[PDB]
Image 1 (cartoon, rainbow over the protein chains, first blue to last red):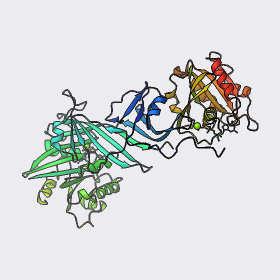
Image 2: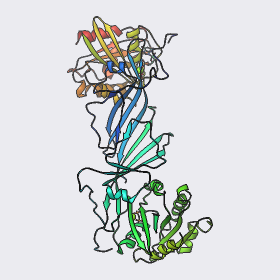
Image 3: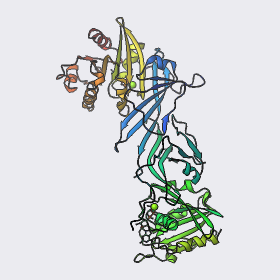
Image 4: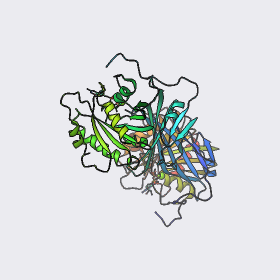
Length: 106
Length: 106
Length: 162
Length: 162
Ligand SMILES: Nc1nc2c(ncn2[C@@H]2O[C@H](COP(=O)(O)OP(=O)(O)OP(=O)(O)O)[C@@H](O)[C@H]2O)c(=O)[nH]1
Ligand SMILES: Nc1nc2c(ncn2[C@@H]2O[C@H](COP(=O)(O)OP(=O)(O)OP(=O)(O)O)[C@@H](O)[C@H]2O)c(=O)[nH]1
Ligand SMILES: [Mg+2]
Ligand SMILES: [Mg+2]
């Protein structure tokens, strides 16, 4: 509720060429027996969200898994941009979600 | 309608160690800008299905793409076993289907 | 010579029965095909490379991936199945209008002629909307896949028309 | 010392306002958080690492991926929003029952106390089912995120009880 300065950029994060990723892969995650596998470049892999890791990177990914109606594992990759803030902290905005599901033909 | 010999095996098709694939990738197929990417081992890559290819391989994959309701590309990986027949031909039985879809967190 | 043939039609039309009757001379028990079958059948010195692709509704959007290189289209129809005959016309026209399937000649197997009150070859021709088509080479062949009737007459029509 | 804080609550409870009031001493315009924020806030020689994860319903299933290593839970409640107070209770209890959140002390910000007819700290306590919980260390802190009232009182409580 002010003419206060914005906290961070909104549009997108492209400070620099190329892209470095925080790959946030929970301990609960198991590797599916799928042909589709995640392929992330210049990635820092972490099991726990970490500020130093976000500080170093431009992009953020969270691997999230649930059991779906038909007893099959459903893998979601939640992706977003990392922004630095006036406070010297970090913000992640989720941009899109990749869902990978399996099913038998019937 | 008889006691005739079975055409082929039905249960499963892994007589040998390792696993060789027919990677049936249509001309119309385009590479998605996704993190999930297909990773097939010992794959023969074809744009057109082909009997000599099925002859050498134990597994079959077809990559199929449609436009989803939200106007997003949806990629489907149709996977199956290749069995040899009494007639000296081939049969492909679809085992499962991996589906890869995108969406904004809206 | 050699010929590449795609065999399509709704589920339970008799495609797999046809393919294996032609190749093994046996009336074998079939399972609904979730996938596809390939056999090479030699008749009148023609090497027919036949592709029997499953017809269950959720497999049909994948039919197009076997179009390329087809010289002969075999479309198989359950003639006793009056409910789904219009649906069958819709699939057939979807196939023959695709760019890859423009040069392929068309053989319709009006199958299950042995069955009580089956639609006759001309009625099939009508209800499949073939009568009008003059720019494509086609023929409706009465058949009974379990006895073998009509089958080799169909393969003969192909032989002549390539 | 250093303390890791996880800050949850339904959407529009005021979590981001709190985070930036504490870090920037400014009442800034917020957008609903589709993702999460991190600020380190230093007060009374404690370095608080605060994770503010968006509360919109399609994000809550993700909350659990931020549980690990959390030393303090801050749960923020809109005290003017009576319709969704029970919903908040459900979410709160869903959080604190997780194995990963077993050792975390619990701070409630009964936020938006400035708003007309706001539910008081003691009413919040009853309606979040806190009164019955005794095997966990919790505290209801009245607060107004836009003015800053109670915020530092809340951080004091976490300091004392860790
Ligand atoms: N009465 C009669 N039954 C037939 C004839 N041809 C096939 N059938 C039977 O119809 C049923 C289905 O035949 P299929 O060859 O498996 O059908 P399909 O075209 O392969 O169908 P999908 O695999 O589901 O795509 C089986 O019971 C066959 O024995 C026929 O000419 N007359
Ligand atoms: N009157 C009043 N308004 C408040 C108070 N705290 C926050 N608000 C307002 O409540 C609205 C939502 O606040 P947010 O901080 O964005 O809530 P949030 O928890 O971050 O919501 P999500 O980002 O969806 O998780 C904003 O308009 C704030 O300015 C308060 O104490 N009193
Ligand atoms: Mg069949
Ligand atoms: Mg927020």
